[PDB]
Amino acid sequence: MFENITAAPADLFGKINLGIGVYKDETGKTPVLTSVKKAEQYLLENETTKNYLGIDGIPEFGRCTQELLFGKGSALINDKRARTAQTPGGTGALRVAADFLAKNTSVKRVWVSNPSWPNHKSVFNSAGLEVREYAYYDAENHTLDFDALINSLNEAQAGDVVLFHGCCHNPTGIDPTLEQWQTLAQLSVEKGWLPLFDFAYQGFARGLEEDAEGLRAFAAMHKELIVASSYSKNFGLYNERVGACTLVAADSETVDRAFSQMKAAIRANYSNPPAHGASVVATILSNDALRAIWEQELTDMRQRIQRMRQLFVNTLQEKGANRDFSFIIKQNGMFSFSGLTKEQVLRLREEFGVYAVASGRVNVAGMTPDNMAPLCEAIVAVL
Amino acid sequence: MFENITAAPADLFGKINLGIGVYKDETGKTPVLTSVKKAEQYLLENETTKNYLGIDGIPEFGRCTQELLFGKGSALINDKRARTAQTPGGTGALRVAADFLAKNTSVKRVWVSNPSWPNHKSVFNSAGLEVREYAYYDAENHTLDFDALINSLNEAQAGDVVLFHGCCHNPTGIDPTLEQWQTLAQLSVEKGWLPLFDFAYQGFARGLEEDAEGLRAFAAMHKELIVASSYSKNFGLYNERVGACTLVAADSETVDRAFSQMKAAIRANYSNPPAHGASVVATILSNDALRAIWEQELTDMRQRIQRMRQLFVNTLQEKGANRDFSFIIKQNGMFSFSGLTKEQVLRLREEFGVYAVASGRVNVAGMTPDNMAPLCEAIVAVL
Ligand SMILES: Cc1ncc(COP(=O)(O)O)c(CNc2csc(C(=O)O)c2)c1O
Ligand SMILES: Cc1ncc(COP(=O)(O)O)c(CNc2csc(C(=O)O)c2)c1O
C-alpha cells in the first residue's frame, strides 16, 4: 500500500534565529506566562474530572472569545448571531471552517493574500477548496498595495471566501488602516464575498480592542462571517492548541442551524477539543485579577517588539547600512519583510549564522538588546 | 451563504445513566486519576515553555506508545518499521489515518463491523472514504458470528482497509479469541487488506499485554498496518485529547517516507498536537513509580467492571429475570448489548428513568453496588 508514496516536500540552526515562529523575551526564552502558571495551579487544585467537553468546548471560553472579537455589548452578541467552537489552535479553527464550508455550502475557493502564512493553502486545499491569491505588498513604499489588492479581488466571484488577517499580517506586518478596512467591508458586501478572518495575533499590533477594529467594521456590515482565532501567541500557549472558530449568521435561528453542521465537522475530525489550554484561557479571561496580569504580560510582549523594531532601525544605521529601514517601525507584530533577497538571506545563514526565511521575513521578537549589534553588522555586510 | 443549510441530525437525563460513554467509579464519579494528578503537578513545577511540539508530538510519547502496542523488544520497533504521531484523541488518530489514506493511497473504502462506534462512518466519510459493513454479532449465542464475519469480508477487495477493534469491541464487548485473531491475520494477508486497528480500551479486557495479542498477531504477519489508539479511557484523560496514529511499513525507508505524508495531513488539520495530556502520559509511562501507580489504577477500573458484570448477572436473577444473562460475564470492557429491544430501552427511560442507547448497549461501568438493585428491578419489569 505504501511502497510508492512520494515524500512530502531549525536543524541547520554568535548565531541567531529570526526564523523562529514564536515570541522570545529579552533573554531569548519563550517562558510560560505567569498568568498561565497561576491558572494551571488553580486547575490542578480544582479539577475533579477529565470528562469530555461538548463538541464546541468550554462555554465560558466561547463567551470570552466573542467578547474579545466583537466587544462587550456588541449587537452580534446581544442578538445571538455568533456561535463559537473551541478548537485545537488557530490551524484547527481554519480547518474546521474549511470542512464546514466545503460540505455545507457552495464555496469552492478561498482568496488569500500574496504573501501569507504558507499553511493557509495546505489547510484549504485539504478540505477540497481551491486557493487564489490577491495582491497585497507594495515593496517600493513598504506598504499595502491597496489598489492592487482591490484590483485582484475584482476577480473574486459572489460566494467566494476572502481571507483577511485581522491584525499583524503574517509575513509582512502591514495591516489595513481603519478606513481601508471600512472600504474593504463595503466592497465585500457589494461583491458577495464571505469574509474569513484569521486572527492569530490579537493584542500584538496596538491593543486588544484596536486590533479588532477591522473585524468589527466587517461585522457591522455583514450578515455572515467566520473568524478563526488563536491564543497560541497572545497567551504563549502554542503547544496546548487553543483557538476558536466563530460562525456569524443573520440571526440566531440560522447560526444555530449552521453551527450544528460545524459541530458535525468537528465530531468527524477530533470529536471534541483539548481542555487544558482553553480552560487556562477561560480561567484567566473570566477572572478580574488573572485577566489584569495577563493583559499586562501581553502589553509587555507588544511593547518589547516595538522596542526591538526601533532598536533594529537605529542599529542598522549605526552599523553602516545607509538604506531607509524606517518602514520597520510602522509595521505590526512579530514579523516584517527585511527587504533582503533570498540570496542575501542564504548568505546571512551561511556566512554569519543569522537565520531568516527565504522571503526575507524576520521575527523581530527574536531580536534582543544583546544580539542586535552582531545581527545588524551581519545584515550590513550582505547589503 | 448559510441561510439554506440543513441542521445536522444526556439532556433528557433514582434515575441511572448507562448511556454514559465514560468510566465511573463505585461512587458514580469520573475522577482524575491519582497518577495523572501527580504527573500534572510535576509538569506545573517543571515546564518552562509552551513552545510548539513537532508535528508528530512528544518523542517519548511515541516510544512508550509503540512499546504498549507491540511489546518491548518487538521486531517492528527494533527494525524501525513504525512511526507514531501523537494526535488529539483516538478520533483524531482515525481522521489522520483516513486523510493520509485518502490522499496518498488507492484506498477507497474501509470495512467496519456491524455494529460499531457510530462515529467511525462519519470520520471515514469526512475524508471521502466509503464505509462498508461486515457481519460480527451472533445474538442467539451472544457471541462473535465468526462465520458470518469471514463470509462478509469475502466481498472486501485487495487494497481495501479493514477496521478491527483491538479489544473491548464497542458496542458488544465481544472480541476475537487469540486463535480467531490468528485466522483473521492470515486471511488479511492472503486477501490484501490493509488492517486498521482502533485501540481505545487497552487494559480494560484482561490486561495491557493480553489486550494487544490480536494486534501483535497481525503485526507478526503484515508488512503494513495502521493503529489508531486512545488514552482517553485507560488514563481517564478524555478531555485532554490524547491518542496516537501509528503507521507500520515494510522497512524504515518506506515508513519514514510514508510518515512524511502523514505529518503533512496533520499540518493541514491542526498543525501539531496538544501537549498537556500526552505529556502526562509520557511522564507516567516513562517513570517506574508513576507507571506502577497508573497500572494499578487501570487494573482497579478493569476489575470493578468485572465485578459489575458478575453483580449484574447475579442481581437480575435475584430480581426475577429468569433469562440467561451469563454472556455478560464473558464480555470485555465497559459495554455490552443487554439484549433489550429499542422499545424496552425506551420504556426503561420513560417508566423507570434508566438510560441506555436504543441498541440496548449498556455501560457496565455506570453500574454500582448502590444502583444495581433498582436497575435490575427496572429491567425485569420490561422483560
Ligand atoms: C496567520 C496565521 N494563521 C494561523 C496561525 C495558526 O495558529 P496556531 O495553529 O499555531 O494556533 C498562525 C500562527 N502559527 C504560526 C506558528 S509559526 C508561524 C510563522 O509564520 O512563523 C505561524 C498564523 O500566523
Ligand atoms: C471504538 C472507539 N474508537 C474510537 C474512540 C475515540 O476515542 P477518543 O477520541 O475519545 O479518544 C472511542 C471512544 N470514544 C467514545 C467516547 S463515548 C463512546 C461510546 O461509544 O459511548 C466512545 C471508541 O470507543
Image (spheres, coloured by chain):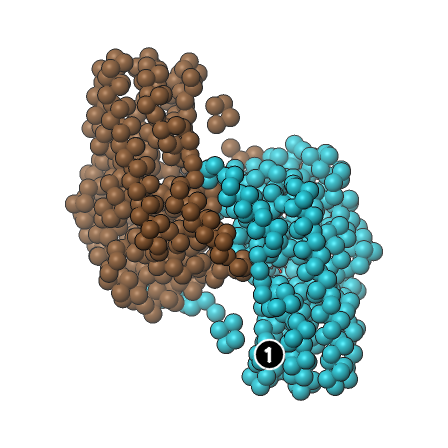
Chain colours: A brown, B cyan
- Residue at the location (75% across, 47% down)? B216
Q: Quadrant of the C terminus of chain A?
A: top left
**Horizontal and vertical percent position of residue B272:** 50, 42
In the rendered structure, the answer to whether residue B30 lies left or right of residue A171 reads right
Q: Quadrant of residue B15?
A: bottom right
Which of the two residues, B253 or B20, is positioned nearer the viewer here?
A: B20
Amino acid type at circle 1 is: Val
In the rendered structure, the answer to whether residue A31 lies left or right of residue B118 reads left
- Residue at the location (47% across, 42% down)? A239
**Horizontal and vertical percent position of residue A238:** 44, 42
Residue A291 in sight in this render: yes
SS at badge 1? strand
Q: Is residue A8 above or below residue A12?
A: below
Q: Within the displayed image, which quadrant is ligand 2 positioned in?
A: bottom right
Callout 1: few (<14), some (14-19), or many (20+) C-alpha neighbours within 10 Å? many
- Residue at the location (30% across, 14% down)? A380
Q: Is residue B12 above or below residue A64?
A: below
Q: Check the image and name the residue furthest to the right.
A: B179
**Horizontal and vertical percent position of residue A332:** 27, 36
Label 1 belongs to which residue? Answer: B354
